Image: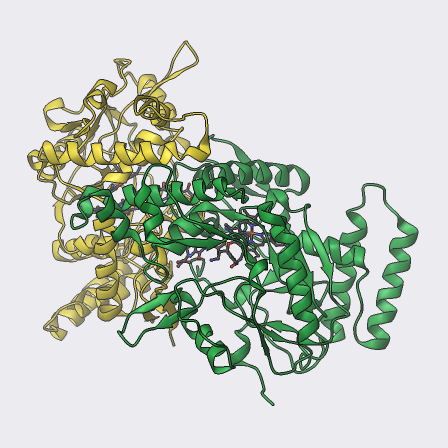
Chain colours: A yellow, B green
Amino acid sequence: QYVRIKNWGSGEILHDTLHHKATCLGSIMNPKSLTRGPRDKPTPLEELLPHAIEFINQYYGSFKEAKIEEHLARLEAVTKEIETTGTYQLTLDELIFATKMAWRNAPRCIGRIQWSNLQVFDARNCSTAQEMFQHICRHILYATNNGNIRSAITVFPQRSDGKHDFRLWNSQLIRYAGYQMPDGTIRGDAATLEFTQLCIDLGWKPRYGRFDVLPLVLQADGQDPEVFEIPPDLVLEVTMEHPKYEWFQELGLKWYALPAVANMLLEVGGLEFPACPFNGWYMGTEIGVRDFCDTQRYNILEEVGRRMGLETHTLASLWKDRAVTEINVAVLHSFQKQNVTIMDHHTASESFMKHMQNEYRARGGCPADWIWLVPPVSGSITPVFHQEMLNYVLSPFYYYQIEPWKTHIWQ
Amino acid sequence: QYVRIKNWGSGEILHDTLHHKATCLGSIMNPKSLTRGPRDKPTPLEELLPHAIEFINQYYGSFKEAKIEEHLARLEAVTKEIETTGTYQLTLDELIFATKMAWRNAPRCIGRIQWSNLQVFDARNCSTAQEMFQHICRHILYATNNGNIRSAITVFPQRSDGKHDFRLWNSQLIRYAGYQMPDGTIRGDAATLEFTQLCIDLGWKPRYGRFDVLPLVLQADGQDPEVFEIPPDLVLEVTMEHPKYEWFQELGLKWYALPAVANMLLEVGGLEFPACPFNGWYMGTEIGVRDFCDTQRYNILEEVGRRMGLETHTLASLWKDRAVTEINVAVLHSFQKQNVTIMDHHTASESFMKHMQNEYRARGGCPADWIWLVPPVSGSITPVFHQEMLNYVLSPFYYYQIEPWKTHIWQ
Ligand code: HEM
Ligand code: HEM
Ligand SMILES: N#Cc1ccc(Cl)cc1O[C@H](CCN)c1ccccc1
Ligand SMILES: N#Cc1ccc(Cl)cc1O[C@H](CCN)c1ccccc1
Ligand SMILES: C[C@H](O)[C@H](O)[C@H]1CNc2nc(N)[nH]c(=O)c2N1
Ligand SMILES: C[C@H](O)[C@H](O)[C@H]1CNc2nc(N)[nH]c(=O)c2N1
């Protein structure tokens, strides 16, 4: 059967079949259903082996020209591998496939039309935190590409017993430090207060700035994490300026060009990769609305309002809506001016709609979390708002993890 | 136990207990879980009687000063009533309580801080469509109050066997007609195309305008529906003007002052009221963003853009965000100028947050559908966006219904 899905803007109807391949608390950010926690022992054969077979089938079934001999031979090899060793190793080709599929299956990602365009750095041979650091640097460097942003993923060694996990303690590859000031005030990124403390506690020298790039906190083979400063030549920044307001530059705002997730787990055919940093390119509203205007972040709304000469004390004036748009054009303008890849939320919405349509035609569905896909600003002025969606967990998938410091056994 | 809920903007944590009193497909507009369909026979005693007792307990348990004698006597009376007659009648006091509770339990309503402030018109003695019409007129008149908008509800007779249902075939008490033009174009409200046809098909004279107020299509005691024109002196309208753009008036826009839902079903202690029109007052973004800017409605965005002299062909310019805000200030300004109650989305968001906080303190929860509660524009600039919510069906509740024309047996 199917689930009937309606696009209220265009009246269009779609039939979801794909939800049958799946594995209200919808407005929860980090639900347990979206988390893949730690392990003390390897995954039971009873659950590993069927998952593995399904992946191999999915992998071979994706081929335009089917190769039955290779498929059955690989099915045989993998089965024998799991039954005798208690685990298995993917081929590079299978890993590349897994990373794209997991992105294709990320319900919270608006940039999925790009799913097939991903550079994969195989770091499964990695053994030390220094080698992890080198892989992360190469990733930052490749992905940054002097502002011509490229989507990439670095896949570190898979979880074995769960006592030898490779982990990136950071939220993101590039992110700013947040300090609780003696004044009671907060400096920089209020969202990294706890993690900034962790870095300081592990020997990081805090420069006490508003835009201090946090260090890499790398855990290799279950060992205690090691702190590494990101070479500043690798961190590309965009200084904020408005195309009409000269005073915008005076706010002294900047942002990093690279949106890279550092802390997620890639699940593929029973295998778990607890260290697999990935990136795309920015969507303007993420910096302009979330990073600059949330009270839990840089919180600049009032200042941009006052400087525009608006009624900052009457909500009914819509000064907040007026200010947010200027911040958003500034973000867009600044990235454009400085030759750095950025996408506006309107263009992204249309792109996702095209992708979703392609996905229903290609496989009878697209897992999509409406709450995440709808831009944080101008919702209904956007096609995705009027689109009914089905949110489900397929495989391969990118899961959240429990924060490493909460489960790590020290030395 | 409880469910831990986080407000990411203020870091605040709440514990939901109330979800235990309840009865992903979250982005679906009219799910079956939110619908209460028709009946051929009265509700089985096995399901009616326990629901009835729970309501009586809830009603008596709401008293500041408990009345055990009255409670047990009413429990006894109701039980005897259901066991012997197969149904029961609420007291006016119980009905008033039920209507407010159902509003308090409406997860999709941002105006809930007002839940206790509701005028209840008891029309349970109604027998004809002409009497229904008189009750609706009195409601429109009371609620309108010359622009000083008051929340009201008219409760028509409860469902008996389901073959004698009282129904309002309209979506809303006041709404504009939508016509498919010979030109292939659409005139007026594109969202009422099908229902406008139904009215024409039932003998309504279409005036072929952009703002033609639809007639009342009233079904009393299971009879065939009757068409009634709303007395125009009862329909208060706000003509749209911008406080700075003189050309805004030239767009020739207007909207009705009264947001009144006509088609929902009130469920209370096993009883179903399939005709119970209710209203509040407008939240600006509903007219400005949804009614004026959706492609499925009045679709004015491009015209407001051009007239502002903007890059209507480059999405990256953020012309849509620029235009929507002006439309929104126009809506707000026009209702203010014309002394008609309206609430901006920023003020409404703050109000709901205060309400939600009061609700967790008062009963350990607040059923809330995030997708609906977050304004259609300026999401994150709003406190409700950062609030994690739990969506569940309590009782009393306002359910959707299957469109009457789809199930009605004609004469
Ligand atoms: C190439 C351009 C891309 C764009 C414009 C894009 C954009 C986004 C945006 C806007 C979000 C919402 C993030 C948030 O609010 O926290 C997101 C989330 C996500 N994206 Fe993409 N994305 C892109 C590429 C990628 C890539 C390359 C992958 C993986 C290989 C990916 C995986 C995800 C995942 C897993 C999430 C959810 C993250 C979370 O739950 O915190 N995206 N993406
Ligand atoms: C007094 C001021 C009020 C405000 C500002 C308010 C505002 C709203 C808004 C903005 C919505 C979203 C509607 C949509 O997008 O379709 C809504 C939905 C709702 N409200 Fe309220 N409301 C108010 C009063 C009421 C009253 C008096 C009741 C019932 C007695 C009520 C019952 C509901 C219900 C049941 C829904 C969901 C309607 C649907 O699912 O289509 N509201 N309200
Ligand atoms: N915009 C954007 C975006 C693009 C790709 C990816 Cl992986 C994530 C993205 O956004 C998220 C926003 C989380 N606050 C993000 C994640 C990691 C680094 C920087 C930004
Ligand atoms: N705004 C608003 C609003 C206030 C109270 C109620 Cl009952 C409903 C409201 O909005 C809905 C929007 C549906 N498109 C509404 C329902 C019925 C008539 C007019 C407006
Ligand atoms: C698909 C999605 O459910 C739909 O388009 C929703 C989104 N949020 C909404 N929120 C409100 N208040 N009213 C609506 O009609 C909608 N439409
Ligand atoms: C409570 C709610 O889940 C939360 O505040 C969400 C809303 N939608 C979002 N959408 C995206 N892309 N990113 C987010 O962080 C959030 N935050």
Work out whether residue B357 or residue B314 is closer to the camera in this orientation and state it: B314
Rendered residue at 53%/70% (across/down): B215
Work out whether residue A183 or residue B313 is closer to the camera in this orientation and state it: B313
- The reply, left or right, for residue A173 in relation to residue A191 is left
Work out whether residue A215 or residue A36 is closer to the camera in this orientation and state it: A215
Residue B289 visible: yes
Rendered residue at 21%/55% (across/down): A351
Q: In which quarter of the image is residue B357?
A: top right
Work out whether residue A339 or residue A128 is closer to the camera in this orientation and state it: A339
Q: Where is residue B231 in the image (x, y as percent from the top left)?
A: 59, 64
Does residue B41 sit above or below A110 in this rendering? below
Does residue A15 sit above or below B297 in this rendering? below
Rendered residue at 36%/54% (across/down): B252
Does residue B277 sit above or below A182 in this rendering? below
Residue A154 visible: no
Rendered residue at 36%/48% (across/down): B249
Q: Which residue lies furthest to the top in this view?
A: A182
Q: Quadrant of the C terminus of chain A?
A: top left
- The reply, left or right, for residue B287 in relation to residue B321 is right
Quadrant field for ligand 3: top left
Q: Quadrant of the N terminus of chain A?
A: bottom left
